[PDB]
Image: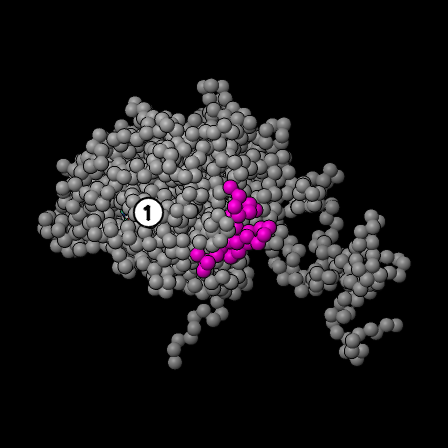
Amino acid sequence: QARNYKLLRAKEIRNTCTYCSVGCGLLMYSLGDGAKNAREAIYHIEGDPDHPVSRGALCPKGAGLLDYVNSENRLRYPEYRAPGSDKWQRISWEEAFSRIAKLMKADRDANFIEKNEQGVTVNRWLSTGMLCASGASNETGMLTQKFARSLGMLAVDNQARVXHGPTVASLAPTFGRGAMTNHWVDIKNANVVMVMGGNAAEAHPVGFRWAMEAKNNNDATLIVVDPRFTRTASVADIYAPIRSGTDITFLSGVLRYLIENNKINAEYVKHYTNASLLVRDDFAFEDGLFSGYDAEKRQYDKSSWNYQLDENGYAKRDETLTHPRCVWNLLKEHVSRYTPDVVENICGTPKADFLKVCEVLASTSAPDRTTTFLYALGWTQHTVGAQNIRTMAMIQLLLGNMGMAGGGVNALRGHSNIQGLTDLGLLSTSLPGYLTLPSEKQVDLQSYLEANTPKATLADQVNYWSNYPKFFVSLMKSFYGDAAQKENNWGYDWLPKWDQTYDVIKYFNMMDEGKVTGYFCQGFNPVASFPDKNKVVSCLSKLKYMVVIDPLVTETSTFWQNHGESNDVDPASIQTEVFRLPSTCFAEEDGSIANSGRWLQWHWKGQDAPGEARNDGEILAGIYHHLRELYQSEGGKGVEPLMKMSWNYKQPHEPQSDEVAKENNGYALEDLYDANGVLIAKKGQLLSSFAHLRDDGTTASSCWIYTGSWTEQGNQMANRDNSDPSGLGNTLGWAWAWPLNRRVLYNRASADINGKPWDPKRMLIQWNGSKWTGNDIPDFGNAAPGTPTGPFIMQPEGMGRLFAINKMAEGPFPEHYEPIETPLGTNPLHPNVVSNPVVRLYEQDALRMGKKEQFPYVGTTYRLTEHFHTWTKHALLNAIAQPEQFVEISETLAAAKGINNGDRVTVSSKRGFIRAVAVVTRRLKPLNVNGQQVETVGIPIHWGFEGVARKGYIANTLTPNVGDANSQTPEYKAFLVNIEKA
Amino acid sequence: MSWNYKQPHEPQSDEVAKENNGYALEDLYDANGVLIAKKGQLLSSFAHLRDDGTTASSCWIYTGSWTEQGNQMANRDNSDPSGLGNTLGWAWAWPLNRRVLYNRASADINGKP
Ligand SMILES: Nc1nc2c(c(=O)[nH]1)N[C@H]1C(S)=C(S)[C@@H](COP(=O)(O)OP(=O)(O)OC[C@H]3O[C@@H](n4cnc5c(=O)[nH]c(N)nc54)[C@H](O)[C@@H]3O)O[C@H]1N2
Ligand SMILES: Nc1nc2c(c(=O)[nH]1)N[C@H]1C(S)=C(S)[C@@H](COP(=O)(O)OP(=O)(O)OC[C@H]3O[C@@H](n4cnc5c(=O)[nH]c(N)nc54)[C@H](O)[C@@H]3O)O[C@H]1N2
Ligand code: SF4
Ligand SMILES: [Mo+6]
């Protein structure tokens, strides 16, 4: 008979995939029953059938986890690379901690800035910066936030900077919050699934099962719009091509089509958006430029981008929508230039295909039909990234799809925990809970609070950010405890104050000028992931010291080592001291991570880490306690802010995940009473809602949107009830979502002004005569139907913005601008303004930009389903599935260059080159754009110089060092290259 | 002598364990007039035992072992939050789940460890 079942007596542990943001459940199997004498070893991993999103399924990345956990390239011991050396030397943990602390202290004491030139206390340290791990837990993230900020760091970013920064920059201004609005299983309710700006069948495969459920079992139409015919196109009902960098034209064309045919949800638009508000008379737009442009600073004065004010100080309105200055009529005028011929001329999308998409989208303007948009980097990674997103969001507000089951904006996050690190604020000027560090002009608490607490711009609105001071003071009580009191303004002056944002491109520009001494890379591989790799390696080489913390060997850790054409450097010329510290991976600790749907999910430890690897919090605590002890005995600069940060863990060298998770939830520091004199919480108890946070020092929380995650009822992130009573796929008992377990944001819009569902088969919330109740937790207060209170409760006007007032850097309405490296060399809509007029482009990077005479083809970079960044090439299973680097090109271009399928080619740009196998296919086809034939060369990003797959070249050797005008997110998706036979 | 078991020829372990823990024989109130236990309920601490005939316990140091919260001797939480190997959630120790006797001496006269 068959071999026996190999897991019958193994230890079974629950955990969550460590790669993308779907958050699939895992069941991991270890050799050993947990007895103290058996050292557990994970030997198989499969899916958890009870998880509501994955239901047992795992894509090739999650299914291959065993080979990542047990990779031959797992890091085992602390290693050190001496200046000008060509080899690693093994050191002890205590030597690593003491050498790093000494280097840090010397640099901090030399360059710490206590006061700025205007006399304000700013306590900031700029010569050492940090990259944080979006693949590590939320408890690691909060420890990293405390470590960084208590030292005064401002150059602190996580992957959000090169990823979904633009989403937050456009979705927050439009709807009030920057996160994905619905959740994976909810996509099954859609009537139309649009995959544009994303490739969900390859980038989020197990979450995409729900789009296949809507197509196959809800009769939905799946549409893919992309320069390439991808694996998501394989299963699509409609495929339409589009030139990289032209989404705003296509989407603005869709707005013009909807308005012109009156394919809108008119009552939704009239009440839930700002359509009826009146805009200042001085607002204008002409020939590519909005009013207020200052051509020398390349920035706009946004004074005119605002509403007209009434007598009470509120925005003026015209409910009939006939006034020439209402948002609705200015929107109509703005998009009138984007006709179907203009879309075809700029995007290259055939009019017949563009028409099919417009007609299907238009069918969801009915109240009981919805479109859901699934997108990610195809829209964010541009110099107009944020504006791409604004256009789509506007479409969803015209169709009335926000707040509906099967509707919304599913901005699919990337890393497993990029949503938690964004929530915890590991971004230059951020604090946890979407709070902001003080700017250096805000000289006291009162100024700071006033700048961050918005006044309502229409009467009768929830305007929930009016509670900013309760969140802020609670954060300060979490950080400083008894040291933060009313008398010292809750420790206000201990936080670093910023003079500007220290985004990654800027900070590498400072590193190139010799202003950066040290850098930490915690679970981030910038040699692979940052634009213009040859410049990145040059900038890192000027560092005096680098600390890498990771479970695997990365290209970044070996940037000083010669790897031939892949990394042609001279070790003897690089003086950086490099510390490589071996950390745990997802399977070797307990903790939480937040998926794309905002679900905070707990996971448990299945084995110890290999060798002398330690957990991320233990590595930060080693360095931190050595450093703070040096300050205790030698003194130095910025002593107080550093020494006042709390580190209240039972074992200070080993902070536990539950202690940190509980601090994020928050506690009552005194007994708390409601207005009726009823006890709401006792001193010492975990809080059950952010509604109980106060601004008087009686409450603490290091992450206000996380209040409710771990209460007196227990760890809600460990809840495993997959019940779905409505049949809509909403499982309120599985894990815990922020905010307050609301799974579908903006769900008051799922009903009309009288409280009646737009679609009676999809009721989310309903009015019972005194409260809202239903199949989801209401994202709303208790305003009764018929009152003026808008459903977007974080917006000061309570509405979805069609016109984004003064929030966007380049305009309150989106406008087409070409990529910095464009194949046309001009912009057919307005040749006087080719590219975004507010883009920041450093002079050194401007010299490294190419033109179409030398680099005639559009270059774009993207992912393949089988690999995750340059991480899974260290896993044998994934290396077998896609072993060797390739690039994709059309049959037409291959014939022109005499390239046969499978031949080697050389792909180059103004910054460098890569060599690879050529995949020649009809899936890529030239498009007719502005009288030219434009070809695209496709460059997957998974290969490099470390790993078990065949050695290749970093794709970022080709990409430009320029980014979105709002978040500085690099333009990785549209640039210019040349190709030659090799 | 009492032999108050549901089957007198086969006294059950839980009946005897509950007698060792002890019971409130009348409703019991603290000095502030707050109910501490109802008549018939298992006591939660020997602090609630009285000398007036309103409480019973056949083993006062065992009060807390099996309360209204259940059999504490069956608790199986091996958590050790301090790292010192103290597992207050595994089984139940006398007296009142104190695992290290004389632990006020683990600090000096001012309370410092
Ligand atoms: N398989 C796999 N999964 C991933 C990842 C991975 O490494 N491997 N990474 C995770 C991360 S961190 C992220 S943020 C996500 C992103 O996930 P996605 O953004 O979906 O994935 P990409 O492949 O980067 O890009 C999507 C598509 O953009 C198309 N495209 C190129 N330029 C343009 C253009 O300007 N407009 C339009 N409309 N489309 C364009 C590309 O051809 C590609 O099909 O993936 C996550 N999931
Ligand atoms: N050309 C081009 N460039 C891109 C993009 C693109 O489409 N085009 N996409 C961009 C985006 S959206 C992103 S997110 C990036 C990502 O690029 P990166 O995030 O730098 O790349 P990864 O290879 O995903 O690196 C993650 C590291 O985390 C380590 N990690 C795993 N778990 C832990 C842990 O528990 N703790 C620690 N300390 N380490 C851990 C892994 O070993 C791995 O080394 O690439 C970006 N760059
Ligand atoms: S990579 Fe994403 S889709 Fe694949 S198993 Fe992991 S979490 Fe699921
Ligand atoms: Mo990403």
Residue A649 in view here: no
Question: In the picture shown, does residue A922 fall above or below A303?
Answer: below
Residue appearing at x 39%, y 63% in the figure: A57
Looking at the image, which is closer to me, A899 or A794? A794
* Amino acid on which disc 1 is placed: Asn
Residue appearing at x 84%, y 61% in the figure: B26
x, y percent for residue A657: 53, 49
Residue appearing at x 40%, y 50% in the figure: A401
Looking at the image, which is closer to me, B111 or A379? A379
Magenta-drawn stretch contains A767: yes
Q: Horizontally, is B91 left or right of A385 in the view?
A: right
Q: Is the magenta stretch mostly helix, strand or loop?
A: loop
Residue appearing at x 60%, y 48% in the figure: A688
Quadrant position of residue A340: top left
x, y percent for residue A686: 62, 47
Residue range highlighted in magenta = A759-788
